[PDB]
Each structure stands twice: as structure tokens, then as C-alpha cells.
Amino acid sequence: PQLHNGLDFSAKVIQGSLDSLPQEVRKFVEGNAQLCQPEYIHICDGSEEEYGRLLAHMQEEGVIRKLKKYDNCWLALTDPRDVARIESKTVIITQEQRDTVPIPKSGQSQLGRWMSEEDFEKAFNARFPGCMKGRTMYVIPFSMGPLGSPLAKIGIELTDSPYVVASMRIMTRMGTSVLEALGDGEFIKCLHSVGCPLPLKKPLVNNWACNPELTLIAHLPDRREIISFGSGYGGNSLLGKKCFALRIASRLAKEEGWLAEHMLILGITNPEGKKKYLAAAFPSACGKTNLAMMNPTLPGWKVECVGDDIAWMKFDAQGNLRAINPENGFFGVAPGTSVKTNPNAIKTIQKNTIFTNVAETSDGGVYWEGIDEPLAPGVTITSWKNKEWRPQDEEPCAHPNSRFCTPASQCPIIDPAWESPEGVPIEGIIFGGRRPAGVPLVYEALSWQHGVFVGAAMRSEATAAAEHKGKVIMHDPFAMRPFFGYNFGKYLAHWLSMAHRPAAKLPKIFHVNWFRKDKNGKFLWPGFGENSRVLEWMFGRIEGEDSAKLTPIGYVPKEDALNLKGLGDVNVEELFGISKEFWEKEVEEIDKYLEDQVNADLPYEIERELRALKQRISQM
Ligand SMILES: Nc1nc2c(ncn2[C@@H]2O[C@H](COP(=O)(O)OP(=O)(O)O)[C@@H](O)[C@H]2O)c(=O)[nH]1
Ligand SMILES: [Mn+2]
Ligand SMILES: [Mn+2]
Ligand code: NA
């Protein structure tokens, strides 16, 4: 209905039909078209034709370049103001702040950012009205999970960015089939704008529309809305990924008895023909993708990848923790990727891949720090800043948080069960981060409650994945600091509660450190495929092997228990050393952090594990 002619957007639809949409989808699309005032509405179909045409259009406009060396690969270079997540501009809206974060004693929380509904309405009104003028609003129906799976969750993302459309086609299952699967069901409402209505009010930098000053990534869990303004960077604009499948989903999971986690899922097969699945939570840019598609150095071992970033898991009636990967692609850090470090990623990204903020070679290929491939004499390099570049120059040729965005189905070791709606049974959970000192290569938690404490106590050097600079060691509990959808204390309680579930077969919990350094700042452990030697030890421990010795922080490998054949130059004593002074300091730091940041919401069990660790260290 309407008394005039501005409410019904039918005449502005350039693909699809508002009449063909499910009723509630139409209302969502049209309501936001009324607000944002796009010139056109394009309902995505997910087809190869749509995708190729959109890419060519972006190429026309100078928004992306085709990489002529490869099969259907593309390179986007962004405004340098829009390169990573911004935690301080990422918020969750609830009636009560304590539902979203524990109230920190110190007054500033490091476990999320809350915004009142009043303040968010004002922020929304200062951003979205008219924001799509002169642009197309693309409507992206997407599934987090295989099309038609009983455990998939569907969303609709509205965006004015073709780059977002193309990247969502890779990272989710997208298009008409999803609308058909959705029918009259519920869907997560996702609204995104780059925040640059036409005619442009401000200079366009590097043909990359964005609004840094007004960037705001908001989540409204009771209304089932995600609303993101001003950034095109995938972590901020691919709304099915961090926003939905971690922040919204972790709160749903709390309410419904499951888990949504920042974890890879991999399957590993040993030389005796046994296969086990493991999950691992490491912070952004701290080794998940490389572990998930590892090429093991140990003969007779094989790793297969289920997912590299997000896991949705629950204990089933048989007691097994079963996990699914709700994503359809990998959005991986590019620098460091080489045939030696991640040969499976190199094979995956050679076709149908979008690269962002990497360098370009004159024969139409890609380049980045650590790529470890010599170029022919005469071949030149254009940096991610679109300037000619030479290896002798002061700055990197690729941004440190540059990315590939690639279909998971193309991974040569994609696991045969990666789309099974039954999920895969997790037998070990691994925590870890970047710790240049003090923390040994691997240890095993003493119990479930100890393992939840180990997750809670995680710390890691800052990376380029968000706004934190330098290499300051930060708390990042469960690798979820940027991603909790609700109060972290409550999340710890939820984890603890799993132990008391009927027939629960609780996975073993481990903590790793690939990143300990010697006195000269060189890594003590080579990592990458050599991490298979650590996974071997974990595998044996899951099977019940007596290959561990007790220490104050947990179980570690016995002398000679790790296979170090071919690594005679590793300094094992240094790499496994546990210093009373370091750990006295560590436990004091963890105590103060949990007291300040979790406070009244810290479960008794976790405080008890803290007291126990302090006491074990005191007996050293
Ligand atoms: N030294 C070392 N670096 C690693 C290892 N695994 C990954 N990296 C590097 O760390 C960065 C992030 O790796 P990635 O696996 O993409 O981490 P993710 O963001 O957690 O998925 C890349 O530059 C990798 O080359 C490892 O075992 N050792
Ligand atoms: Mn991640
Ligand atoms: Mn990754
Ligand atoms: Na650009």
C-alpha cells in the first residue's frame, strides 16, 4: 500500500522480482530501499553469468584488475584506511550492558563493545538515510552451510558493493536456490553500505568507496539484525562470517546448547590408518589456515581440511562433539604463503580467486612477502599501493593483512565430510597464539575445567588483522576476544557446563606455541608442516598413550616422545623450558586480568583453576 508512489520499489528492480520474494524478504528489501534510496535493486541469482559480468564491470570501472597469469583471478587494491577489522568500531546492542560484556572493574572492557539502543539509533540515522543514492542495492540470499542442510542458517545481505557480492559468492552459498530453501522461514537481516552516496561528497581514493570516519559494525541480536557502515574490508562487510557466524551465532548457541567458535576443523590420518578430527582456536593471523590445510612432513600422515576459521559444534545424543564448517571458502592471509609453507593453499588460489591488497607482477601474477618464488629478469612488480616496487625498498609490496578469497571446494585436501550435515566428531581442541617467550611448544590440559581455563588465559602478540599495532601481547581468550556475542563470563560457564552433559565424550584440550623465539629473535621451531610432529603426539595422547609427563602447567611430552628425526638442530630444552619466574609473573597477570575484566561473572571453577596453577608454580 501507498498513497503516492515512493514506497513500492518494483520499477527499480533490474534483476529478479519483489513479487517473487518471500513476504518478509520483500519487506526487508523494500524497507531498506526506502531508507537508503538506491537507484536500482538487483536480486542476486548466484549464477556464473552474474558473477562474471559483475567482475568485468568492476574491471571496467577500475575497481578491480584481472590477473592475466591465472584462470579467472582478480586483484582489488583498497583505500589504505580500510584494510582490516576495527574492534573499537564494532558493537553489540542490548538493553543491558552486562548481557553483552562483563562490567570491567577498571571501566574499559577488552571483551567487546556495547552500545545502547538510543545511541545506536542516533548513529544509524547519521549514516544510512540516502546512503545508496545513485547506486545499486544488491540483495544477496546466502546460506551458512550446504544448501538445504537442516543445520544451515540463511541470511539476506543488502549491500551497495559489487566487491561484497563477489566475495560472498565465494565465502557462502549464494543465490536463487537459497531463496527457494528459505521459503517463509526466518533469516538473519544483514544491511551493509560503503557510505558514499553519489554524487561523491569526498575524494575517492584508489577507486575504493569507504567512509572511515563513520565506520561502524553493529549487531542487534534480539532483532536478528546486523548493520555495517563505511568499510568494504571482508571482516567488516561479509556479514555471514564474523558478524553472523560468530557474534550472533555464539549467543544463539548459548541459548540453544551448542557452540560457535573461532576454530579450524581438520581431519588427520596416521600411518596405522586411523583418522581423527581436531579443532583449533588461534587468534586472527596466528596459524589456523596453515594448520587446517597442512602438508605434513612426517611420512604416512595426512591432513584434510574441513574449515579454516569458524566451527559450529554440539555434543550429540551419543556424546560426540560434532562440528560443521558454515563457510564455503577461505579468506586467508596472503603474506608468508609459499610452496614450502602452504602448498595446498597455493594450489587452491590459482583459479577463481579474489586477492585484496597484494602486489602484481608485470606478467599478471601476484606477489607478497614470503612468496619464495624467483621472478624472471625483466619482470617488474607493482605494490599494493599501485606504485612500482623493488625488494630493496623500505616497505612491503603487499599489505600485512592482504588476503586471498578462494572457494573451499578447490582445496586439494578438502575433507570428504566437509559438507556432511552430521558434522565430524572432534577428539581434540587446540588453543594457542603468538608467545615469543615462556610458553613451550605443546602441553595438555589436566581436565576439562583446566582446559577451559587454558582457553580463558590465552594471550598472543597483536597482528595486522585489526587495529592493534606493535607486537604487544594481548589477552585473546578462546581466540574470541573480537567475536563474543554475549558476556564472556557466561560463555565460560557455558563451556564448563558441557562436562556434565549426558554421555559427553569430552575432547582432550591442548595448548601450542609455534612462535617461541630465541635470544636473537629467531623462531625455535620451524612450524608449518613440521607441526605434524606435535599433532602426532596429540593423536597418541587421544588414543591413551602414556607419552606425557606432568608439569605445573599441564602434561608435556616425555623425553624422546616427540619425533624430531630430521630436526636435530632444534633446541628441545629451550623450546620446552618452563621457568618459575616467568610463570609466577604469568599467573599474576592472568589473575589480575580475570578479576578486572570478568569479575562478578567469572565462574568459580575458573578462579579455582587459577588458584591451582598458582599453587603448582609456587611448589617449583
Ligand atoms: N612461523 C610460523 N608462521 C606461521 C605458522 N603458521 C602460519 N604462519 C604464518 O602466520 C600468518 C598467518 O597464518 P594463517 O595460517 O593464515 O593464520 P590464521 O589467520 O589464523 O588463519 C601467515 O603469514 C603464515 O605464513 C607457523 O607454524 N609458523
Ligand atoms: Mn578468523
Ligand atoms: Mn585464516
Ligand atoms: Na582500487
Image (cartoon, helix red, strand yellow):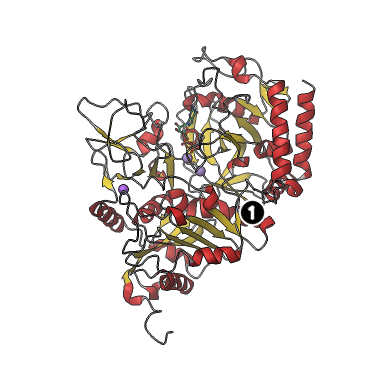
Question: Going by the picture, which residue comes out furthest to the left?
Answer: 378
**Relative depth, front residue between 523 and 318:** 523
Indicate the quadrant where residue 348 lies: top left
| Residue for point 62% across, 18% down | 561
**Quadrant the N terminus occupies:** bottom left
| Residue for point 68% across, 41% down | 505
Amino acid type assigned to the residue bearing label 1 in the image: Tyr
| Residue for point 77% across, 41% down | 605
Mark 1 burial class by Cα count in 10 Å: few <14, some 14-19, many 20+ = many
The answer to whether any part of residue 515 appears in the image is: yes
Instruction: Pinpoint residue 328: horizontal percent, then vertical percent.
Output: 44, 49
**Relative depth, front residue between 328 and 240:** 240
Ligand 2 near label 1 (Cβ, under 8 Å)?
A: no
| Residue for point 76% across, 25% down | 617
Indicate the quadrant where residue 367 lies: top left
Instruction: Pinpoint residue 467: horizontal percent, then vertical percent.
Output: 50, 43
**Quadrant the C terminus occupies:** top right
Instruction: Pinpoint residue 158: horizontal percent, then vertical percent.
Output: 42, 63
Q: Secondary structure at mark 1?
A: loop
Instruction: Pinpoint residue 79: horizontal percent, then vertical percent.
Output: 36, 47
The correct choice, above or below, for 368 with respect to 22 in the image is above
Left or right side of 590 for 187: left
Tally of marks:
1
The correct choice, above or below, for 94 with respect to 454 in the image is below
Indicate the quadrant where residue 133 lies: bottom left
The correct choice, above or below, for 388 with respect to 94 in the image is above
Question: Going by the picture, which residue comes out furthest to the front?
Answer: 202
Residue at which label 1 appears: 486
